[PDB]
């Protein structure tokens, strides 16, 4: 949802 | 004053949409699929194997919805009553047999509400209110034993479509080109074809072998082309690689040519296959004949099953090999098994056609043994 | 099904303004906003009561038995 | 890294290349097999200098690999290293020669020392995959960080 | 703040320049691969670092603004529900969607949706959602955010199962 | 670049044979007894790093392909500004992101690769 | 299988799937999705050879590489040089109604292939057709205000129908497979040749290639999601 290295 | 040729605006969209829903409503996928069954598919099934060793089936008629009464006339049946009275909103099936020395009732077909065959399809608004059926019912379902039943669309992969796939680091096969050919009508004989590329990058002589049905061994593709009448190397590679300049692809095949050297003619080719599909006591001709029939009916059936179409399959087999190589050469990515364009959604229509076929094939078996069990059908469908 | 007797939130009697409201639209060709204020529905709780109601009884009455 | 060398971004690079596995496949541009009959003079123009320069049994078939200088000096590799590695791979069962580190092209030439063209394609393969030029078995990527 | 929204918009507009230049660079074959990485791997790497820096800085700009009256901020200052990431997606940029650790893949041949052209690695094409929830998402931003959304639902199902068996 | 030949008579693949006495390369058939001399001495070539495939797809009707991006660079030949461009059609991970343009006026293929290392792009 | 694929756009709702085990395996068709019912290919396969499709039995590749190969329902029926005019015709025929709208025809120019689909089970949706047959300006949607007036004219009278639009080449049906070969405009407005700061930010219309235009983007949604207010301001899950 958020971005790469985070949630989708 | 409002130039009819003036560009359209974003707001003008809903008009085009309302028009869409005004014509199809919300469950046209259901209705349309089922109507296609009743109207066309139903008949087409009565003509497949519509003959026995004579007795042949002719035309089909689908009654409006009626009820089988115990101690009573056959009544007309309206959905509202079918629900309440735990019935099955179905209509009778009548065929047209031709008994030749060498109508007729045949089962009940449950009917989808609001389909051409249903009583509510032509009903006006007040006709509905009198019939105790909400004018808001969209109806893409069936009424079986009193309960409303829906056939959920079953999604599956499409047929007759080449697809190459890489393979797990362990297996001896580095790539596979697959097709699951089947016939549109008649009987859907789905005999899978697999063109495998043996050996991983860096293995010695990566060979290509196909997998024919009923044959207990993968056959080098060159032997198959020759079995199909295409004998010389040059001619075979020409069906695979369509560019005389693509030395890399041509090079990937060198080991294929070598792998099929021994077999230098159509008969020896056919015998080669016939043997991997026949016991050790069978005479040459029978073997060769076995391989001919296989390549004719079990091999790439979606193309043809008739006779003089060997060149048509050689080019298609070559096509598959082309696409397989095009992937092994890192020039195309292996096919995406999740692309929706290669899926298909089965609905009431298609679904109802598998049962009906199979069932009609049982009713057709019994006849080979007015001596007609109508229940074989009305039960299977209802079941 | 039918015009609620009163406004859920405050109690205002509203079960007596449905026919009026209906006429205020057809025969007087007014708009729901103006129509509602002229029926005395000033606070939005009572407004929504009518502006949002759905007279489904009219459809039930169309059934024979 | 060892105690007194944790800041030398350069010793870190050396150790990286000494651990990271490296086969000939990772440094080769292309491989070819030529019919080059006269072990002395060559059919290939560019390699005339390399054969003369090597004077201060063999089959007529030639295996010729073209190595890339980038991946080369990158993984800190010498023509002499790569070559001496291949040679000490195929005992006396293979004639090996290679251009020098100054020549503009990195090229290796090998001859089997009759079903030749075949043995060669197998040998060509063994080289690109089974020969370790430098590094440890299994260790593939090797990244530095601070 | 009216001004903050201008600052936030430009902050992203700046990231699309940084990403646009790394493209021209890479399209010229000037990008240098980081040892043990493909050009394309390090290319993506940078675009993702760029975009995230944007998302982040866009979020702080929004965080800083909110007064003490701001109820969302009041909840955060106390501990009860809400974090930076939440305020940031509502007010400033929503962020970059992603499935399996990468930007939205070319489902169609060489493109994310049939509305783009082939070989479009721009942020708009590959899943960066510029708008906040407040501003609303565009159809493309919406689908991409649903793709990312589904990934979470899927392994919330998995993660759920796999843990009830491990604990046992 | 091992462009190989087939038999004159039977159209079968030819194989590399050595004339030991005169030390030269021949290609014989293994079906009949045909045999010819060789064009080049190159018998086999394996490109670990390849370029072929990059340009695949440059067809005459390539400009009518609506999905393709268009630019207005200048082709080194006719200087026209009607271009259609795509990335490398090879499907390797170790590929660059260089662009290949196609002059829609004279169908000339040019690149954005500032390290242009080839002349034909084939 | 349970992941939301790109090719699901417009055909299956991106939001309505059940949580849990059936997640992503149980889908819902978007408001305007339909499913092919099936058509006979004979007519098409006949027209094809009447129009220059060389039979596979007489196809020699080294003698015509540039040839495009044609497939119908998976069958490679033949080859055809200059397929461009055949494709123009095929589309015109379908836009008349001489070829069933339901039929999917795709031309992959770079791949030298032309594929036709007549089988049942293919999911498709309707899009506005955009061609430049209009002199006055540039490329425009073939549906004009005059058409919409007739549509609404037939509404108010409760005869210009959805089928009329199909018959007059104004709208087309499109399946995921064909969707591959086209470029779609999101809003008919970005076919056009100091900004409200409250609006959401959007991208440009650098497209002089548009072949179609979405009827309305909110149609990617299914029935359930079509009831959520402002679903585009909500978190995905
Ligand atoms: Zn009130
Ligand atoms: Zn011969
Ligand atoms: Zn030019």
Image (spheres, coloured by chain):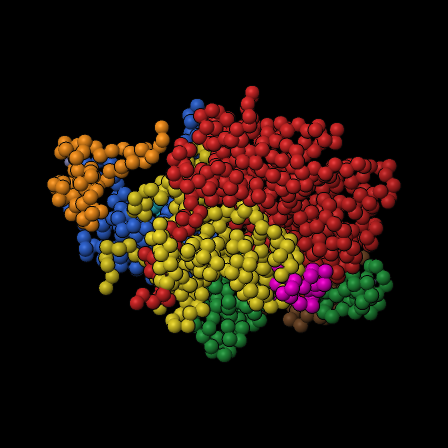
Q: Quadrant of residue G80?
A: bottom right
Total marks placed: 0
Residue B146 position (above or below residue E90)? above
- Where ligand 2 lies, by quadrant? bottom right
Identify the residue at horizontal 58%, vertical 65% (top origin). G86
Q: Is residue G159 visible?
A: yes
Residue lying at the far front in this picture: please name it.
Answer: B73
Residue lying at the far top in this picture: please name it.
Answer: B71
**Residue G53 among those drawn in magenta:** yes
- Colour representing chain G: yellow
Q: Is residue B362 left or right of residue B122?
A: right
- Colour representing chain E: blue
Q: Which chain is cyan?
A: A
Q: Is residue B340 left or right of residue B262?
A: left
Q: Nearer the viewer, residue G89 or B213?
A: G89
- Colour representing chain D: brown
Q: Quadrant of residue E44?
A: bottom left
Identify the residue at horizontal 64%, vertical 55% (top origin). G42
Q: Which chain is orange?
A: C
Q: Nearer the viewer, residue F37 or G236?
A: G236
Residue F120 position (above or below residue B163)? below
- Colour representing chain B: red
Identify the residue at horizontal 50%, vertical 52% (top origin). G175
Which region shows up in magenta?
Answer: G48-70
Residue lying at the far bottom in this picture: please name it.
Answer: F78
Q: Is residue F114 visible?
A: no
Q: Is residue G138 left or right of residue B196?
A: left
- Colour representing chain F: green
Residue B236 position (above or below residue B218)? below
**Residue B4 among those drawn in magenta:** no
Q: Measured from the top left, where is residue F88 in percent x and y? A: 52, 62
Q: Measured from the top left, where is residue E154 in percent x and y? A: 43, 38
């Amino acid at each position: 949802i958020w971005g790469i290295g985070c949630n989708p | 004053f409002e130039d009819e040729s003036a560009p359209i605006t974003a707001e003008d969209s809903w008009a085009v949409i309302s028009a869409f829903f005004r014509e199809k409503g919300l469950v046209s996928q259901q209705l349309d699929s089922f109507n296609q069954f009743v109207d066309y598919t139903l008949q087409d099934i009565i003509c497949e194997d519509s003959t026995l060793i004579e007795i042949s089936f002719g035309k089909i008629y689908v009654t409006k919805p009626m009820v089988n009464e115990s101690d009573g006339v056959t009544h007309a049946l309206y959905p509202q009553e079918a629900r309440l009275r735990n019935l099955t909103y179905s209509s009778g099936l009548f065929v047209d047999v031709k008994k030749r020395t060498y109508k007729v009732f045949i089962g009940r077909l449950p009917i989808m509400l609001r389909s051409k065959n249903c009583y509510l399809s032509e009903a006006t608004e007040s006709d509905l209110y009198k019939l105790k059926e909400c004018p808001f019912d969209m109806g893409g379902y069936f009424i079986i034993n009193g309960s409303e039943k829906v056939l959920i669309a079953q999604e599956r992969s499409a047929g007759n479509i080449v697809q190459v796939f890489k393979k797990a680091a362990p297996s001896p096969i580095s790539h596979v080109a697959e097709i699951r050919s089947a016939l549109e009508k008649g009987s859907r004989f789905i005999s899978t074809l697999q063109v495998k590329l043996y050996g991983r990058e860096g293995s010695s002589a990566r060979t290509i072998k196909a997998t024919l049905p009923y044959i207990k061994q993968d056959i080098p593709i060159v032997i198959i082309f020759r079995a199909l009448g295409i004998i010389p190397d040059g001619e075979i590679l020409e069906h695979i690689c369509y560019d005389v300049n693509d030395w890399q692809m041509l090079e990937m095949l060198k080991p294929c040519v070598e792998d099929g050297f021994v077999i230098q003619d159509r008969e020896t080719a056919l015998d080669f296959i016939g043997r991997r599909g026949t016991a050790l006591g069978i005479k040459k001709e029978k073997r060769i004949q076995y391989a001919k029939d296989i390549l004719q009916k079990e091999f790439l059936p979606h193309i043809t099953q008739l006779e003089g179409f060997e060149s048509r399959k050689a080019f298609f087999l070559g096509y598959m090999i082309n696409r397989l190589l095009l992937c092994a050469l890192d020039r195309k990515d292996q096919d995406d098994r999740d692309h929706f364009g290669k899926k298909r959604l089965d609905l009431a229509g298609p679904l109802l056609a598998q049962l009906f076929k199979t069932l009609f094939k049982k009713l057709t078996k019994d006849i080979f043994r007015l001596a007609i069990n109508a229940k074989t059908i009305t039960s299977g469908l209802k079941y | 099904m039918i015009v609620p007797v009163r406004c859920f939130s405050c109690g205002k009697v509203v079960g007596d303004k449905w026919e009026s409201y209906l006429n205020l639209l057809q025969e007087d060709e007014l708009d729901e906003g103006t129509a509602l204020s002229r029926l005395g529905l000033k606070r939005y709780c009572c407004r929504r009561m009518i502006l949002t109601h759905v007279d489904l009884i009219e459809k039930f009455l169309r059934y024979n038995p | 890294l060892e105690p007194g060398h944790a800041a030398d971004q350069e010793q870190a690079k050396l150790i990286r290349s000494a651990i990271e596995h490296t086969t000939l496949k990772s440094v080769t541009i292309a491989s070819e097999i030529y019919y080059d009959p006269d072990p002395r003079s060559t059919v290939i123009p560019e390699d005339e200098e390399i054969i003369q320069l090597h004077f201060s049994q063999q089959s007529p078939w030639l295996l010729r690999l073209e190595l890339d200088r980038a991946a080369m000096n990158d993984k800190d590799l010498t023509m002499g290293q790569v070559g001496e590695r291949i040679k000490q791979t195929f005992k006396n069962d293979l004639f090996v020669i290679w251009s020098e580190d100054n020549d503009e092209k990195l090229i290796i030439r090998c001859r089997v020392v009759a079903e030749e063209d075949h043995m060669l394609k197998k040998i060509e393969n063994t080289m690109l995959e089974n020969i370790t030029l430098r590094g440890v078995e299994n260790i593939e990527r090797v990244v530095m960080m601070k | 703040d009216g001004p903050t929204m201008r600052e936030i918009t430009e902050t992203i507009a700046e990231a699309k320049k940084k990403v646009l230049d790394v493209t021209k660079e890479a399209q010229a074959n000037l990008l240098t691969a980081k040892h043990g990485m493909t050009l394309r791997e390090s290319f993506e790497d940078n675009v993702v670092r760029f975009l995230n820096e944007a998302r982040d800085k866009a979020g702080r700009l929004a965080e800083v603004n909110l007064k003490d009256l701001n109820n969302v901020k009041q909840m955060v200052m106390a501990g009860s529900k809400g974090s930076f990431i939440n305020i940031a997606q509502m007010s400033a940029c929503v962020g970059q969607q992603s499935v399996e650790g990468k930007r939205i893949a070319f489902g169609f041949v060489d493109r994310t949706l049939p509305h783009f052209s082939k070989d479009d690695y721009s942020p708009e094409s590959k899943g960066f959602v510029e708008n906040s929830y407040l501003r609303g998402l565009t159809p493309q931003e919406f689908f991409f955010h649903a793709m990312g959304g589904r990934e979470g639902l899927i392994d919330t199902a998995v993660k759920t199962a796999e843990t009830g068996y491990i604990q046992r | 670049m091992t462009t190989f030949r087939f038999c004159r008579d039977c159209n079968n693949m030819l194989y590399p044979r050595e004339d030991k006495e005169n030390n030269r390369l021949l290609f014989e058939c293994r079906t009949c007894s045909y045999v010819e001399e060789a064009g080049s001495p190159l018998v086999y070539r394996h490109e670990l790093i390849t370029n072929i495939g990059e340009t695949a797809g440059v067809v005459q009707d390539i400009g009518s392909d609506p999905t393709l991006p268009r630019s207005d660079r200048e082709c080194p030949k006719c200087h026209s500004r009607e271009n259609v461009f795509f990335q490398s059609q090879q499907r390797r991970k170790d590929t660059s992101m260089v662009l290949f343009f196609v002059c829609l006026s004279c169908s000339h293929i040019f690149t954005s690769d500032q390290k242009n290392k080839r002349t034909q792009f084939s | 299988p349970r992941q939301l694929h790109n090719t699901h756009w417009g055909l299956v709702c991106p939001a309505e799937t059940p949580e849990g085990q059936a997640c992503g395996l149980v889908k819902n068709l978007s408001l305007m999705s339909c499913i092919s019912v099936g058509t006979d290919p004979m007519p098409i396969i006949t027209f094809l050879s009447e129009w220059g499709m060389e039979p596979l039995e007489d196809y020699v590749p080294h003698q015509s590489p540039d040839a495009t190969r044609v497939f119908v329902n998976g069958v490679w029926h033949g080859v055809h040089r200059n397929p461009a005019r055949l494709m123009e015709t095929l589309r015109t025929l379908r836009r008349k109604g001489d070829i069933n709208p339901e039929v999917s025809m795709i031309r992959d120019i770079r791949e030298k292939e032309l594929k036709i689909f007549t089988d049942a089970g293919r999911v498709y949706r309707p899009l506005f057709i955009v061609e430049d047959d209009e002199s006055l300006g540039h490329k425009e949607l073939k549906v004009r205000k005059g058409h919409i007036a007739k549509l609404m004219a037939t509404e108010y009278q409760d005869e210009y129908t959805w089928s009329s639009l199909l018959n007059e080449g104004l709208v087309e049906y499109i399946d995921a497979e064909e969707e591959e070969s086209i470029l779609i405009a999101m809003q008919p407005e970005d076919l056009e040749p100091d900004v409200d700061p409250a609006k959401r930010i959007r991208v440009s219309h650098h497209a002089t290639t548009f072949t179609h235009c979405e009827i309305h983007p909110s149609m990617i949604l299914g029935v359930a999601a079509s009831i959520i207010p402002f679903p585009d301001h909500n978190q995905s899950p």
